[PDB]
Structures are given as structure tokens and as C-alpha cells.
Image: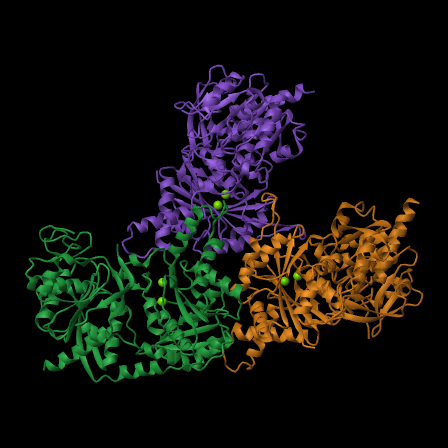
Chain colours: A orange, B purple, C green
Amino acid sequence: MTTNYIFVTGGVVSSLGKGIAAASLAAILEARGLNVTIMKLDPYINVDPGTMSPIQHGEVFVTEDGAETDLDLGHYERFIRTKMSRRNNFTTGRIYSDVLRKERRGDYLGATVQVIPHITNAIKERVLEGGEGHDVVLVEIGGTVGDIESLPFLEAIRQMAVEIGREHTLFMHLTLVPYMAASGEVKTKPTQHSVKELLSIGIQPDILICRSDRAVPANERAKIALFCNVPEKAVISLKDVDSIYKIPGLLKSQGLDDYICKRFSLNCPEANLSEWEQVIFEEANPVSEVTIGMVGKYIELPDAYKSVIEALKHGGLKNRVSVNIKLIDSQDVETRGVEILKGLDAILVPGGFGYRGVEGMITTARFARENNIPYLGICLGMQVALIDYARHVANMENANSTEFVPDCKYPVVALITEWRDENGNVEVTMRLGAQQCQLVDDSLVRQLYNAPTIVERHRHRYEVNNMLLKQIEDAGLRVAGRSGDDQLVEIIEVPNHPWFVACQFHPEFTSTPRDGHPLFAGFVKAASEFQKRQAK
Amino acid sequence: MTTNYIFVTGGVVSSLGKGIAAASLAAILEARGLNVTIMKLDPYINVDPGTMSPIQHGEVFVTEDGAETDLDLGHYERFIRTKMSRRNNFTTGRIYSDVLRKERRGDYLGATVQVIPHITNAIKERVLEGGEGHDVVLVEIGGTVGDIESLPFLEAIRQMAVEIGREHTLFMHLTLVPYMAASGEVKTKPTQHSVKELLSIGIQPDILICRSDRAVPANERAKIALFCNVPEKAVISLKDVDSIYKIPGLLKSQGLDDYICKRFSLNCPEANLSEWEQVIFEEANPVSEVTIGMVGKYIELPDAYKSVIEALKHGGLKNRVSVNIKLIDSQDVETRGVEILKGLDAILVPGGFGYRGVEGMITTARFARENNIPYLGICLGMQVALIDYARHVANMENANSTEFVPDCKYPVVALITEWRDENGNVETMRLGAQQCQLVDDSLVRQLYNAPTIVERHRHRYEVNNMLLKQIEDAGLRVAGRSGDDQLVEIIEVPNHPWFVACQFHPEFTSTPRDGHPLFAGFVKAASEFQKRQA
Amino acid sequence: MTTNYIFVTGGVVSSLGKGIAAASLAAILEARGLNVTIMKLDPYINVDPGTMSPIQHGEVFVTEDGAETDLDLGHYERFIRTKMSRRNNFTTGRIYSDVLRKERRGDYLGATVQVIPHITNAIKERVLEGGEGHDVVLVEIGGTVGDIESLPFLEAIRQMAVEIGREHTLFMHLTLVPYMAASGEVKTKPTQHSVKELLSIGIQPDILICRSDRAVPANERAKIALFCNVPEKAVISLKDVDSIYKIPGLLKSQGLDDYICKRFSLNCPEANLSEWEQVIFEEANPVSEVTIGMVGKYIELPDAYKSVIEALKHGGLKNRVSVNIKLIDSQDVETRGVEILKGLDAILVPGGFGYRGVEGMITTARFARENNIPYLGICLGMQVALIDYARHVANMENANSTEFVPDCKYPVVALITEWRDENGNVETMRLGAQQCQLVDDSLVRQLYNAPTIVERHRHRYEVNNMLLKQIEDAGLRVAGRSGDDQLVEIIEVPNHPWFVACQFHPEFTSTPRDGHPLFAGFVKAASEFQKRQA
Ligand SMILES: [Mg+2]
Ligand SMILES: [Mg+2]
Ligand SMILES: [Mg+2]
Ligand SMILES: [Mg+2]
Ligand SMILES: [Mg+2]
Ligand SMILES: [Mg+2]
């Protein structure tokens, strides 16, 4: 099993759908029984995305193993079965980070450390390390062919190709092909110029995925093929679709996989896109429609909630419900009232950090609870839910979490190390990654999940204060799931509501269009049910 | 009078509307009382545009001086009052052609002839020659930056700038700023890559014209302004508009002219855009509408009849009528018959060459003439009508133009030389502006409200004077003539609401601001018809 | 017979000796029994090299077929046996000139003519035409990579390679590898930058010829091989040698041909360089030496007489004499007189045009003739002698060539047409190979050991036959003639040790391997003289 590489680059413009296109291609190949993987090389100095701001960067994906990563890894997982690890994503800064240590520590032997080969060498090592024992490895180069930031990545993959050879390496480049209103036509120039840059640095693309408003007409394609470029019938059209679930099919329709298998000398069964057609079908044929309110502090960048939004969609798939997501700002709530929340068949409070929109969230939770509106809260969203209750259904006077009010009488949520009493009494940090969790017999989730135990992914520090727990419990609230050790609280549920659950983890990083998510499926169904009784 | 030069280039993709944008800028400057001109440098080996196909290039504009040029000079002309000459358009081929010959006549003295400096020197010569004593000269460079084709032009203007200095030189570069439905955002990378191709060539742009499908936001702009670009507040947004007549105003609103004037140290009044405003108003507030059928052969590529279409639009303006142009292929008249002609308030038969739909046209002329439908025929459209007339009225069995049936007995159209008769009895090309005399009791005389007019020519075949009288007798009216050989220019059909046909190309003189008497009159009639006919 | 193409380009600087290096490689391949040719693509607008000045370009080589070409074809010819035709050299100007005309005759059908594909198509056509059925074709691209001038040629060959594929195409790129007296080391950066300019243009070199003043060390090489370059062991060192005759061996030692043959899948015997070895030996082991004065006008740029110099060198080879060429300006003969001629064992008066030193020459001829100094005159050098002879012996007051004094009474040199007499009595250009008949009792007859020979021509002015007999009578010998008009080709001076003068350019046929009878004979004599004269 000689490992084969597909280096995926984009030209002309950013935001071309490269992540998704690699994902889709990976999907097809897997559908052919191949052992496939994908990796993301991010051309930025930040050592890890775990510090990038959601606005700008988008959401911070979390792998099983706790790596904080680029959201593209989210796309990968929702398209292929291979699990992502830290090995699947690295940035220009971690490389440098690396090379700078080895240096300042000898390794180089007073030799002069340069981009080439020291940096490039470091890139290859990591690329190999992640391709390690896969039939096909998709290497997605972030940024745009043409930026400097890209340079070292491109040079490294160039080196690889030479080394490894045409028989186990391919270059897949993505270009924009604008449609002209004025021209009333297809502009191929930009692709030519892009391919031109590849050549300028040693790279001759083997495949071209042409992104356009609409399908790129053979004639145009035929032009590109030869037009500079120089590919054969490996010029692919990637029109704008209304559903990403259709991409694997479109690419297949065009022979991309075949081209790829031949080149790689991969003898293998024809791709069966049944699951994808299924997903498409379901999506195309909803029965009912709901409107869900997503109440958070980062709505400027919807990509800040990428995984949630996809999860909601999946939940809809599993119920034949067309979900209408209405993005709402924690703030306005605690500003514009509560009349913004009205008209939601359901309400979701995602994660985030601060204290910023936090008050409006607490509110939202209360509104949901009080108005028997199905509510689902992730992390922050659980916390803001622990509160409202603590506050409104118990004593917990000004109930809060030390993230916001370090000195509260009632710190129902806060670092374990900070666990104190209402009387300041006391007892005798970053949770990242997949973690087992024990569900409470007789709980909603225990039913939804249909298992005693589950594994979910975390990304948090502030825990439920066990010190003020029973106090909230006895107020009626219920603990649905825990995480042994310190038995930390993972899931809570409010007993006298139609559908009210909250968890510490990010159920969203486990949802997929093909298999859904028990929690989201439930939530969505409930939303439906709610819609149904509100009028009938 | 130190001449000032504005070098206009384009990046990313072709078709950014660079010609119109240059025209519009010229329009502002002119509206500030400046003496302005514009020139088109086409990076193509064809020596003379007058040989290229419309499929590819679209209409052949004709200047006053008879030069055959790129359609862009038509745009220039519809935006500024400066007239175009053969000196406002030239190609790579002309340059090489020039150098080759100069070289063959030993002007170079055994020295090595090279792109640099021979070709570039030749280009510079032409530029200066064309900008000769104007306050501002806009030099539009054809082609797309980054291509091989335009290299010489770019090197040449680089030198000029360097020679002339930044006090009288500016580079204005158009670029595509795509819109991502996805991210819902605007991509400035292409601009950056494009701007960098200039640098690689030694040019650093002074102004950027950012073309998008919507306005480019100050955000995306200041980014451009600096990031990879380096211009001041010379980052201009040029969104897709619904009327090119809005452009000068749009550019003026963003201060382009001020920046321009400022750099060139031009102290002049603010741009008075009143005429443009009027045009804009008239266009937006039609009081009625019509459907004018445009019956021809190159009907496929629109640009083929750029100027005609524009002149019909101007006709609307003048009459506050909304003109619906129905592009009709003459072969289908041939094919399916006058069935297609049904539903028009007017019929226009344009010029062109190639027997092709020629029969399809004659028919149309007839149709129009026989159904009292207002008609306008230009050149071929006039010939096509002489025929119909001659035929169906003068009874001249298969009257024709030698151009298509040299053996015709009855050939009312033909070179002055081939001029024979039905009895075989007997006894170069027209280009550019020609005085023509209007006949005293003509419709056309009224419209133009003048004894003599000046129009543009581009034809060989003529009204066989040896047969004229026959048709005259048969009722036809000679509305105008050349003068000397007293060649027939215009003809009229008396028992008609509105039937005019001329040899010249009236469309080359139409302007949105001042319109055109024929077109005006023709549109009016189309209206009248419309109404009546209901 | 799938033709194989070797694209030869150059980077960093011009004058890397690219022509010689291509020739030498061709020489190896040929020595392996391959059918090989070479062509010169000159990126200059001059249509015909036959109009460029030597100041700039050096001698005008003349092919068998009469084509006037770049001196490089002379190099080609001195290294391979394949003969050159007009098809082995062409310029940018020829290409454009071709396209222009094709375009004017509507071959393009109104389509846009552009650099790509029209010009590039034209180039490809010529290349294929020139490589037509040879096993290997070396295509030398003139100019320096990275310049604008050579763009088209580079794009064209890029296409070919792409079209033809790597099985029959190779790119060979010459580059400068400077030596730093400082660090005492060798700089490979320029190679890298140069190699990268190719990439930017879409070409990735297969072989690098590293030119230095000393051999490039395996060290600096493997670095090149990979670092920024990417070729295999196609990194060749080409140090400055003392004899170009060593080159094929030097290249062969590094395995260039094997690599070449290998890539092209050519199965052929090892390069037999015996002839080269001999040449090398002869050159290194002269047994005596001489000083031959080369008396002329363009005396300044050496390359002006490339072939002559080479043929004199070959003369040495054949006689194991070391030839000391004394470049003597004819105006100084004019200026300072025969004083300068002192110290020569022989006198050579080359060809050329321009009255200039013409008098300086006639003198020389005389001097040589009157001091029994072996002489050789080519073309002008022959004319210059007819004169002297005619004059100082036939007593023809100021005999001359109309070329300089059209009004001369006594004009022994002139166009067949101007052919008059002293009494005014009476009754295009020669280029390329011409049969000439050798006179039975001539020296020249012995030397060539043949009745008829073939030589190359490049002249207009001729031996005025109406005056011949006079000079014949005065003692002069007609050693050879054209044939038909029985034009005088060669003349001899009987009371002389060695005095020959021909119209043709013997130098165009000289070769280091096979030498040249005239030159051989002439050098021999110079030796003899030398000795005697002491
Ligand atoms: Mg991506
Ligand atoms: Mg990235
Ligand atoms: Mg234009
Ligand atoms: Mg153009
Ligand atoms: Mg050379
Ligand atoms: Mg050259």
C-alpha cells in the first residue's frame, strides 16, 4: 500500500470551497473502499487555532484527541469516516516553532538554518507523518497560490512530488472562473494566470477544479486544458450548488475519481454514492418546517458556529423537518427585551467566552424554560441555564460563574479550584477532547442516546460547582449525565418542560449528515412538536 | 499647455468596460472646460481594423477622416466632443509594419532593430502625436495586463512616464473585484495579483478602478489602498450600473477628477454634469414604448451594431419613448417569411456586406413599405430598398446589385464602373465624412433642417444612375446626393408614413446628448404608428 | 526517424559562447553517426541579416543556397558536415513580416492576429521545416532568457516540447557561473535566478551548461543540480578553453551525448573524436611561425572577419605553422604608408564594401606584388589588385571600380551593365555557391587539383571584360572564370612567389578538419618566405 498524495491548492480567490471539495473527493474515494485521509496546512504564524478569534477564524474545531483546530477538520469528519487527530492540521508557526527549538538545542549543528531545507524538511516530516498508512492522502494547502505565506508549503509539496514521483502524487488546483454580465461570458484568464504561478515555482497542476456561477462549458474547459494549464480531460467544473451533499456526485459525474484511480493505479470498485443520495433526498423532501433561534454573542461570523448549524440541519434531516435557523444576539435580548425570541419553535444557546452577551443568554434560557419552549444549550449555554434556575428557581440570589463575577455569593459555575460555598466554604483545568460520560437512568438523554455511556468532545474550564449542586437539584433541576473522577456534571435537564437539555460538551462535533446526532434529532423533533401544538 | 497623460490599463479579466470608463472620465474633465482627447492602443497584429470580423470585433467605427477603427472610438465620441482621427487608434501590427518598412529603407543604418527601443520608440511617437496639445490625453491600453500581447505598449508608456515625470503622468488601472455569494464577501486578491503584474513590469499604478457587481466598500478599499497596492484615495469603486450615462456622475462623486486635476495641477471649475443628468432623467422617464425590429445578418454578436443600437436608444431619449429593439435575422425572413415582421412599430435595416440574408432584407423593405411600417435603411439597408422599390414597382425583373449578381440586366446597385444598363448599355471606396445635399422638398430636408449635411461613409456599391430615372419615374424620391457625380445618398417613399434610406452611417454621429435627426424622426414615427395601430 | 529536438538557450549574460557549444555538441552526435542539424533563431526585427553592420553583427555568413546569415552558421559549418540553408537561420522580423503579409492576403479571415498563436505558430512551422528528417536538431535561441525580445521563440519551443513530449525534446540552457576572487568561490545564484526565469515562462531545463573561467566543481554542481535547478547529472561544466577544438571532447568526457542519446533512445556507437584529436594535436605542435598581415577597413570588430581568421588558422594547422595575424587598417597605409607593411611574411586583403580604405588596399596589393610578398585577396581584395595591376603595369591612369569612381575612363571593376571602356565604348548580385572553372596552367589549378571548383559568392562589381585583355597583355593571369558570361573569378601574378586573388569567399568553405587549398597554399608560402627572408 504505497501511500498516494493529492495536494489541494486554490488559486485566484480564497473562499473557493476547497475544504469542502477535498472533503467531497475524499468521500467518493472512501465510497470506493479506499483508506483515505485529509490534512490541513494553515499558512499562519499562530501556533494553534485554539487562540484564533471566532470572528475572523470561525469556530475552533476540536478533535477526539483534544487538538484545537481549523474548522475544515469539521468538514473532513462530516464527509469521511476517518477520525481527525492533531496530525491532521498544522500551521506555518508551529513549524517555525519547531525548527526554532531543534535549533536552539543543537540539532542543526552550528549549520545555518534556512527556509530550505530546514523549514521545508519540517513540513514534509509532518505531511508524511499524517499520511502514514493510508491509501490516499489529501493535502489541503491553505491560503492562495500566490501569497508568500504559502511559499514554504508549496515548495515542500513540490519536493515531495519529485521525490515520490508522478505515480503517487497529484496536484489538484482550484480556480475562480467569473461569469461576466458585461462579457455575458466565461473568463478563463484568471485560471491561466493562476496556473502560471504554479509553474513559476515548480508546480504543474495535474487537475483543475473550475469554480463558477454555473457549470463551465466544455468549450471553456477545453480552452483551459490546453490554454496554458496543459491538463488533459482533468479539467473539472464545480458549479455553485444548493447543497454540499451533491458535490461528491457532481465530481463523480465528471470522472474525477476515475482519473485519480488510474493515475494512482488503483484498481477499485465504482463509487456507490447511496448514502449521499439518501441525504440529498431526505433534505429535498421535508415534511414540516420549524424555526429555531440560535442565541449567542458571535453572530457577525456565522462560521463561528459552523458545526452547530450543520448539526441543526442534520437533526432536520433525521426528522424530515426543514429547519429555519434564526441567528440572535445574546445582547439585544438583554437590551431589546424578549420580543426578539418570540416566534421560535425552539432555542439554542451555543458556546463562547467572556461575560459579554451572557446576561441576555441567561434571559433566553429563562424565557425558554418559562415558556415551555424547547431549549438546547451547549457549554456556555448550559451554564447560562444552570444559572437562571439557580437564580429564578432557587435561592442562588445573584447566581453566576466566576468567569464573569469572580466574587459572587453564588458561584454555581466556576473552576474546580475555585469551588466555594455561599458562605465561602470549601473542599477537602482545560477539558479538551473526547471524553466518556455516564448517563443518568431515567433521563431524557439516556433515552435519546439509548446507551448508559457516551463519548463526547470537550473544550472548557469552568465546571458546575458541586458545592452548590444539591441546592439547585432540590429546586427541581436534574442531573442527566456525569463524568466520573470528580463526578463532574455534564448534562442537566429541567423536569417539567417539553424538551429541555443542556450539556457541557459539544455534541455538534459528532454530528454528521449521514448519521445525525441523537441530541439534535431530539431537539428538532421537539421543535416540530412544539410547532404542531402551537397552532393545533 | 504641458500635455498630461492618463494611462488606462486593465487587469484580471478583459471586458471590464475600460473603454466606457475612460470615456466617462474624459466626459468629466471636458465638463470642467478641459481640452481632452482619448486614444485606443490595440495589441493585435492586424494592421487595419477594417479587416476584422464583427464576430470577433464587433462594428467597424468610422472616423471623420475615413479611418476605420475599433468600436471604442464610437464610445469616445459619444462622451466627449473632441473628434477622433486615424491617429486615435493603432495596433501592434501597424507598429511593426512601420518599423519593418523603415528598416527596409535603411533608416536604421545596419543597426540591430529591436523591440526596445525601436518598437517602443515607435509607440511613444504615436502617443505624443495623438496627445499633441491637449490638456489631458487618455491613453487606453487594450488587452489584459500580464499578457504577452501588450508588453510593448506597457514598456513604452513606462518610459513616457519616466521621461515625462509624475507631474503630467498618471496610471489608471481597472480591475475585477469579485463577489463571493458564499462568504458574502468581496475578493481583493485578484487586484493585488494584478497590481503586482504591473510592478513586475516596472509600473506602479496611481489609481484603481474597482469593478464589482456592487459598490466596493471603503473597507475592502482601504485594504486595497494599501495592502498590496500602494495608491492613496485613488481607489475608486465602479459598480455595475444600469445606464452608462450614470458613470461620469458616479466617478465624479468619488472625486476622481479632483484627484486628477490636483495631480496635474489643473485649476478648473467643477464638472458641470447637467447634460448627463438630463439624459439620465429622460432615459428613466419614458412616456411610451415601442418595438423596432432590427433586421440583419450579423445579428448574432450585438457589438456588431453597437452604434446603431446606441442611436436608436438616443432616438428614444429625444422622444421620451422606450425603444424595444427586436434583433431579427434576415435569413429567417427568407426562411419563415414576413410572419416574423409581425409586431413591429418600425423596421430598421442596417448596413453590412455579404449576399447572405440580402434577400431576407429586400423582403423586409417591401413588407415595411407595403404595410406602411416606418422604415429606416442604412447603406445596405438602402440598397436592399432600391431593389424592392425598383422591382415590385418599376417592374424591373430581379433588380439587383452587382455585388451579389454581377449578371443582372437590372443592376441598380454597383460600382460606378460596372455601371451599365438593361440593354448592357454604358456611359474606389467611400470612407469618412462627406457633404451631402438635401433635396428641397424632402422629409429628410425638414428633419435636418438644412440644405447640406455631413455624414460618414463606408461603402463601394452605388445607385446606378443609369437606372435612377426609371425608379424615380416609378414614384421613388431622391432625397439627397453626394454632389459631383451627384451620387444618390438618400431616397424616400412618398406614400409612406415614414420611409427613409441613406448611404452614409447616420449612427456614427448620434450622441446621447444631441441625438440624431434621422433616428429622432424615425423613433417618433414608430411611436405614432404604435398608437394609431390600435 | 522521429525527429529529436534540443532547444539551446542562454541565461545571465550574452556571449557565453552558445553557438560554439551547440556546434560542439552537434559535432559529438555526428561523430556517433547521427544525422544532425542546427538552426539559429535570432530575436531581432531585421528581416535579413544581410543588411546589418559588422560593427554590430560581425561577418555576414553566406550559405550554399545564397542565404545571408548570422555568423553562427559559420560555426555550425566548421563543426558538422551538414550543410546550412536559408532555413537554418531566421529572425523575429522575418516572422512578423511573414504574418503581416499572410494577414494582408486574408489568410486569417478577419480573425484577430496575435502573438499567440499566429506568431508562435509561424515559428513552430519554421522549426519543423528545418529539422525535417534528421535524428537530432539543435535549435539555438538567440538572445538572453529574461528579455522581452526572445519571448515568442521561448513560447513556441515550449509548445513544441509540450506537443512533442519529453521523449524527443530536451532543453539545454547555458549560464554564467562567476568566480569570486574574494571568497575564492563560485557563484551559482545567477544560474538559479536564470533557471527561475525559464520557469516563470513555463520551461524547465533538462541540462545545464555551466560556463566559468575554470571548471565548475562537483560540489557547486550537485548544488545546482538540485537546489534551485532540478536537473539530473545534466549539470555540465564548460570552462574557458584555449581551443574550441577541445570542446567536443570536454563535453564528451562529461557524458553529455550519452545523456542525450539515452533520453532520445538513440542506440549508437561511441563518439569517434579522432579528427578533433588530430586538430588539437596539430594546433599545439606548430613547427614554425609566421606573421600574416590582414589589411582592411572593418578591422575594428574582429568578428567582422570571423571566417577569414578561422581559415588562416586552419592554414596553419595544415602546415604546422603558427599563424600570427596582424590586423592592419588600410587607412593607415593611406595615412602612414607601406611603412606598416614592414614585417609580414604574407598579406591578406579581405572583402568588404565602402570606398573607405580602398586606396590603402590597392597600395598594399602593389606593395605585396612589388616586394614579392605572398598575397591573397578575397573579393574586394581581388578587385583592389586588378586595379594596382592594371594601373602600375598596364599603365591605365587611375584604373578603378565604378563602385567608387563611376566616372573613370579606366574602370576594370563594375557591373556588367556599366561595362564601358576608356573610349566610353560599350557592348543583379552574386550570392551562394557557384561553379567556377580553373584555368589549366594555373597555380590555383594545382592547389585545388581540379578542373572545376565550387565557391561562395557575395558581390556585385565585376571584372570589366572590355578591359581584361589589356591587363592580360600587361602580364596578368586569369586563373578562373564563372562560365557563361565567363566572368573572371581568379587572377594570378606570374613573377610572384605566391599571388592569388579570387572573387568568391574561400573562407566560407574552410574547415579545421579539412582545411582549404587556397589558405593552405597561402600559409605554406608565408612560411617559405619567412625562412628565405633570413
Ligand atoms: Mg479550506
Ligand atoms: Mg488557512
Ligand atoms: Mg476597451
Ligand atoms: Mg484591443
Ligand atoms: Mg550564438
Ligand atoms: Mg541572435
User: Vertical placement of A486 versus C46: above or below?
Assistant: below
User: Horizontally, is B506 left or right of C443 in the view?
Assistant: right
Q: Is residue B28 visible?
A: no
User: Horizontally, is B7 left or right of A501 in the view?
Assistant: left
User: Horizontally, is A374 left or right of C222 in the view?
Assistant: right
User: Vertical placement of A190 versus C265: above or below?
Assistant: above
Residue C330 % position (x, y): 15, 64
Question: Which is more toward the observer, C496 or B201?
Answer: C496
Quarter-wise, where is residue A81 in the image?
bottom right
Residue A217 % position (x, y): 64, 52
Question: Which is more toward the observer, A387 or C477?
Answer: C477
Which quarter holds ligand 1?
bottom right
Question: Which is more toward the observer, C164 or C441?
Answer: C441
User: Horizontally, is B278 left or right of C289 in the view?
Assistant: right
Q: Is residue A93 visible?
A: yes
Pick the quarter of the image with the C terminus of chain A. Answer: top right
Q: Residue at x 40, y 22 (%)?
A: B483
How many marks on residues?
0
Pick the quarter of the image with the N terminus of chain A. Answer: bottom right
Quarter-wise, where is residue C372 in the image?
bottom left
Please, which residue is most extreme toward the top here?
B441
Residue A526 % position (x, y): 88, 54
Quarter-wise, where is residue C450 in the image?
bottom left
Residue A317 % position (x, y): 83, 56
Question: Which is more toward the observer, C96 or A243?
Answer: C96
